[PDB]
Length: 189
RNA sequence: GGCAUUGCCGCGAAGCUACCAUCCGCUGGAUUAUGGCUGAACGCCUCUAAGUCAGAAUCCAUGCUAGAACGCGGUGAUUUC
Image (cartoon, rainbow, N blue to C red; front, side, top):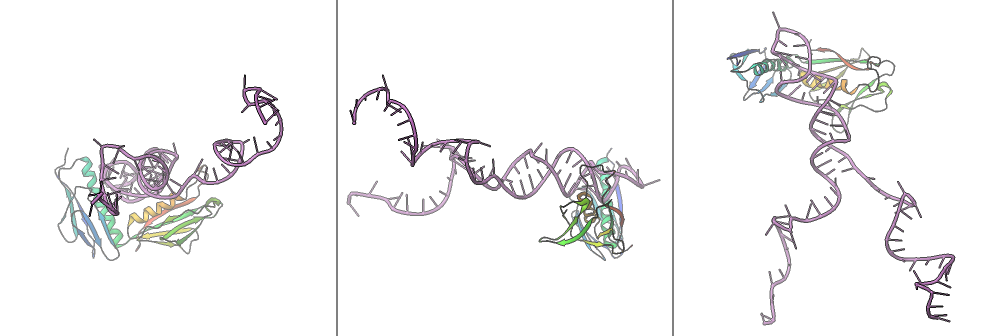
């Protein structure tokens, strides 16, 4: 039933600093600074070393032990986007009507717009999330490479363009037009 | 000028009136269905378990009507001298 002890270990890379007090994880490193708040989990961190953090739990059930290894992976995605970073290559697919994507800075921030998506006359606004720079691949005419130091604000922004460029009232297996993600790489690789 | 239970006919202002006439009828947040993201369970996978995003003529506000005659606030003046 309730497992008496369940531990995981977060290997902390070189040059990377981690600051934890009352389940708030501030990570600084060679590029970027990430602060994720974890008050919703009963989890005890402990500094067993300067190179690796032990994360443990006590008397947890199957529900709670399952929500322990999701904590190690969330810190591991924090330090990985802080050492290397994250970049998402996205790709334009269209049958006839070309998609024309730009970047505009309106009153608030860098809205992303698409125009002529399947011949449509309505622009499709989608804001950037901050910490994410927006990049176009110059060599390939139909490509877009999102990038940033958090995997969350990139991938939510990468799924934002997938959600906004959908089809309506047609066969999706015939009308396979849209802006899909193909590659989820790191920045320094 | 009277009377004809407003004698009858034509025009008729005021008033009332008619999609028979004209004018007017608000925009913000959260969400269901559903599509997603990060990601475990289950050394893979997964939209869900912990998180999170987009979203219905829906919902709660904004707006509109009443104002508790036992809800309340602020000010004015307070007697024959």
